[PDB]
Image (cartoon, rainbow, N blue to C red):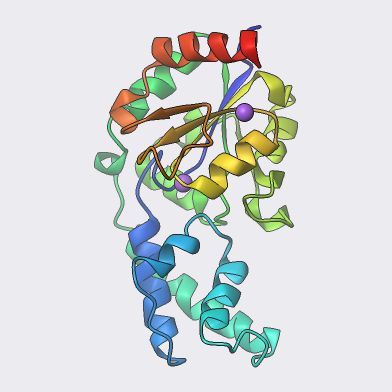
Length: 225
Ligand code: NA
Ligand code: NA
């Protein structure tokens, strides 16, 4: 019952991008009479670009009032602004304990994957300086279903050519945790316990993501699954 892989989400596990997306979406949203707050945005978190835009427009009952071309234009302006913000990310922005985890996973001959809904995930990993640590990066551009649908996590399992039942999925949002469990994987949640209650394991912060602790908990889950 050995682990075949650790599949990570990007935002809130490898590094923090949620605030940058929010700053970028907030600017475009104001231009259509919609002012999103860090509470509403918490439902745009880990969501793909065009879906995220539709939810923002929805919030103002104008999701169906724009043509997709016009939505394409709006998305572009937002993307350019988001890309400008993340281009200042460095290795110092890697969440605490992640590098050490990435190393230990690799020393235990276990694959590593990233299942992020962002087509900017590659750009971010290169700025962090750890793109070489990832065996497979799911292409959000080919994913047709956002979390909590398990597609993005199944894509990394397919990509790495491993059994999802032997995979560990790490995430900080409830939608992602639902996607991980729906992919029949061991789910590890990072953050608030109440919001991440459906996770198989919940830790407080990325510093709590220790390899031996994750493995001991994984073995427990497998025996009881
Ligand atoms: Na996340
Ligand atoms: Na599970």
